[PDB]
Image (cartoon, coloured by chain):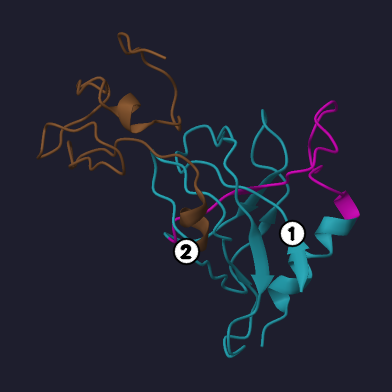
Amino acid sequence: KYSSKPYKVDNMTRILPQQSRYISFIKDDRFVPVRKFKGNNGVVVLRDREPKEPVALIETVRQMKD
Amino acid sequence: VIKFRAGVCEYNEDSRLCTPIPVQGEIEIKPNEEEELGFWDFEWRPTEKPVGRELDPISLILIPGETMWVPIKSSKSGRIFALVFSSNERYFFWLQEKNSGNLPLNELSAKDKEIYNKMIGVLNNSS
């Protein structure tokens, strides 16, 4: 395997620790954190951007059970 | 007690025509928690909360001797349930299953004789 220029895909994609390093922060993706430098493994954090409107939502299991 | 399926539309009233939106929702008929009110209540099942509007599991109450049953208020759409209130922020319903729409609609919603014996009987009955 090797590494190349990252390209955009849909939501809910499998991302390895080498795969997340190429994630770029662009206002099109609505990434505005406090750390501003990310792409390690695990779960990231997205700070509130515009309080007037939400970012987006996807149907998950936690929404129904919690 | 009796399961029923319906939906909601917007609040804008101009020509009395409200175009339904594919919003997932369910309403159930239960009198009360302690049954101390004396009349059946119309609630909203917490199914989905689409973004872009204000939707919450809010209940609804009916006042006997006031609300009258109109079979349809709309000349374009069909199966529009009309419950007239006074400044109560009316919530319009609609019948999910489609039994009609290919014929002119005057008194037709579900059945002329069957529906007329439901909402009128519940209106006069109060506990």
**Residue at the image position 73 percent from the left and 48 percent from the top:** B71
Q: Colour of chain B?
A: cyan
Residue type at mark 2 is: Ile
Residue at the image position 84 percent from the left and 34 percent from the top = B100
Query: Which residue position holds label 1?
Result: B4
Instruction: Please identify the dominant SS of the magenta region.
Output: loop
Horizontal side of A13 relative to B105 (left or right) equals left
Q: Nearer the viewer, residue B25 or A2?
A: A2
In the picture provided, is B15 more to the left or to the right than A2?
A: right
Please give the residue where the numbered disc 2 appears in the rendered image: B58
Residue A49: image location, x then y, percent: 17, 36
Report the side of A62 relative to B37 (left or right).
Answer: left
Going from the N terminus, do you reach mark 2 or mark 1 first? 1
Q: Which residues are magenta?
A: B88-113
Cβ atoms under marks 2 and 1 closer than 8 Å: no
Spot the brown chain and give its letter: A
Please say whether residue B6 is one of the residues in the magenta stretch.
no
Observer-nearest residue: B96 or A38? A38
* Left or right relative to B31: residue B106: right
SS at mark 1?
strand
